[PDB]
Length: 506
Ligand code: NA
Image (cartoon, rainbow, N blue to C red):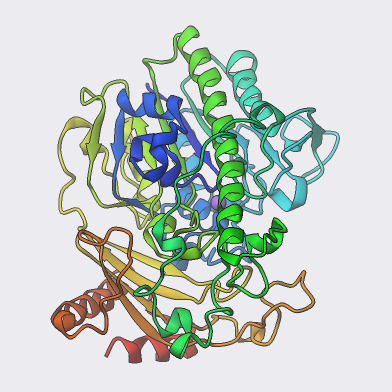
């Protein structure tokens, strides 16, 4: 039986992996991950269905869309009973281990072993982190706490190596979820990376300074009346929260301020990515010397993408390419296609059924996702989707990003900004409750955005109001309407929202 190590980093976006060939690849940000891809298979079209940490991690654990597993936003939690991925590996006779960033709210009690960050409600600390572990029995969750000195990414790797070396029953296969907290904000990189990239300019995206044709009334207001309201920024654009403010840039020139904030944002972030990559070298080295390299499936992914200043945006949540796409690399030692790429349209909800089938199990019939394990034997899965669904539910909270649904085909992306919160008690409350002058949660404008992701991969040009694209827009609206029906996301429980979305889709 094959062992499995599922490695996932927090907010590690595809621009920041060398193998994905973004503007950042010239910096060689992830040599170890790149080498893994050269001996594995890289997936070009892997998409989150809902880009924030907790909803994505719930989709991964349950194989189910947010509207099915009910973990809609960061405000909801998983139930232990919903730990389906690990239940399935248990039922197949695996010993199971959960290491690192959990962030699902509940105890990882369906694991045989866990040691997961607890600082700041499951967010963890970059230095001297404490962990909740199934080894502390003197106390009950969430109080079975231990503390480790030093840098988190180094400690996380040590927890995994320790379990493999000292705790695993070598007579049984293992399934391990190995989750780094880096490169999540605040990007507190380890001191030894202080001068990494010191002499280099990080390539700047044109869209940081030019948004002329991007967006719509739903993301900008009419005539940009909401340009300082919607969407936190790298520049001074967003009036409440942005990196120019956060990094205290004040050169006398706002464009220079933006450039300097982008450089500090990207360099701090990439120094955290480098710490993860260096740590992967240690882990992979260990697996190789232990004789596990050729009997262990290894996955490397990030729970969602992140806006690294494209369109002058930050964080995730948006359906735009950099936030929707997850990097996703799998090395199955039995797969003969080494260094291959796959363009199959996949979602984070497909991870669990695929892994289960990879080791000989059956695709679970209660999951929304399906298994693409046949790709590793050189065959597209039967009747596989050629489009993906997306919905961000957490209207305006944290980053002033309006709620939206969308569909991405291989050629076009249609986004419907419906601009409502599913819990109308939240209207009027602060979107960022730690700030005295936060904006308030309010309904925003309904609008469509249509991007040609093949000829405009950076989503520079919203086509929804171009009359040359009237038929494409109608065709994609029909597909969005049907896909929403196909996946069961029809809002009978939220009639406020159902009326708005049904009306917009004709
Ligand atoms: Na995340």
